[PDB]
Each structure stands twice: as structure tokens, then as C-alpha cells.
Image (spheres, rainbow, N blue to C red):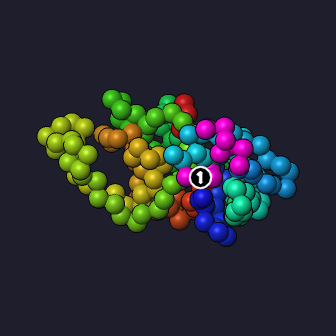
Amino acid sequence: VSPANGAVVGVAHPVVVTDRRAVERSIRISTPHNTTGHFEWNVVRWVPHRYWPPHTRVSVGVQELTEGFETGDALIGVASISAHTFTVSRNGEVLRTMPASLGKPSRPTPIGSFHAMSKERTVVMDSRTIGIPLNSSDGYLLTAHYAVRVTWSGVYVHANVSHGCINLSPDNAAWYFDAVTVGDPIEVVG
């Protein structure tokens, strides 16, 4: 079961647990206002309906085991294909509307509602590593700085960008990296 014990995460962070109805029954999310959500699939995860309440203690019961974590500030990022922005708000107020490169017109950033999965100060991205040659237009070999993993499928926040990834200036990517915490909502919309 993840997040780990005591871990202070953001508000889009799902709980991950490693008959489909039968293990669902053996799990329950206990919150101060009994927050509702649903199961999504092995390994099953539970997502809150409109997020977690900020600064709320969450405990997960799964069988004879209970574990609990905390939520911090409500820091929300929204990526607009059409506005060409990444906008980061924290508790209502917006901190930065930042210009962003969201994929490329061939492969723009996939619409969805996600969370920051991890933080890596620099990450090298070689298309050869997943079977894509460098002589391709959708090919690359670069070091990404201040990379925040959006999806399992390879979107990173870190312009002809491939894999759907989100590109910002270094000043803005550094800040978001500073601002963001594991769990924070990243929203891809129009």
C-alpha cells in the first residue's frame, strides 16, 4: 500500500493497493468528513472524487492492516493546449500562469487529470531506450532538468516536444519543481 507511513502528499494522490469485488470490500478510506471516491484498476487504486481535502489526515484500511498519511497545501496545475499555458494555483489564488509547450501538434499533451508522480533534478531521455531511432522527427536524446513525472506513460514537466511532455522555461520549471510535492494535481484540459 502506497503512500508510505506518515508521508505528506498532495491532494490528487491516489492510494495504491497491490474476485475484483472481493478485494474492494477489504479496503476502506477513513477521513474526517468521510470522503468519497472510486476504485480504478494485480494492483487496484482508489481516487478521491474531487480530490483530498487539504491538510487532512487520511488512513487506509486494507485487511488487518491500517496505514495513514497527510495531505498538504492544495496546489493545482492546469495545462491548456489552446491557451498554451501551465497555470499553478495554490489554495484558490493563482501563483503563476506559465507559458508551456504541451507536446507537439502531432502529439500534444494527452487530456486527463493526473498527479505529480515523482521529482528528478535531471533526467536523460533517449528514444532508443523504448525503440525509437534518432533520425525520426519524434526522436530525441536530451537531459531534462527539473522533471516532474505526470503519467506512467512518460509525460514529464521539465517547441517540438515528443512523448506529450510539458516544456517550460528553466525559471518556471525550477519554481514548479520547488513548489510541487508528490501528489499535487496536474490537469490537462483545453
- The residue positioned farthest toward the bottom in the image shown: 6
Q: Position of residue 16 (x, y in %)?
A: 59, 52
For residue 17: magenta?
A: yes
Q: Quadrant of residue 31?
A: bottom right
* Quadrant in which the N terminus appears: bottom right
User: Which residue does the image show at 48% across and 59% down from the upper left?
Assistant: 118
Magenta stretch in the rendered image: 13-26
Q: Which residue is nearer to you in this view: 23 or 181?
A: 23
Is residue 186 in sight in this rendering? Answer: no
Q: Position of residue 57 (x, y in %)?
A: 76, 62
Q: Position of residue 175 (x, y in %)?
A: 51, 62
Q: Position of residue 64 (x, y in %)?
A: 71, 61
Is residue 7 in sight in this rendering? Answer: yes
> Which residue is identified by label 1?
17
User: Which residue does the image show at 67% across and 41% down from the upper left?
Assistant: 22
Is disc 1 placed on a helix, strand or loop?
Answer: strand
For residue 186: magenta?
A: no
Q: Quadrant of residue 181?
A: bottom right
175 sits left or right of 93 in the view: left
Q: Which residue is nearer to you in this view: 131 or 142?
A: 131
User: Which residue does the image show at 60% across and 46% down from the upper left?
Assistant: 45
Q: What is the three-letter code of the residue carrying label 1?
A: Val
* Quadrant in which the C terminus appears: top right
Residue 77 lies, with reference to residue 57, above or below; the image says: above
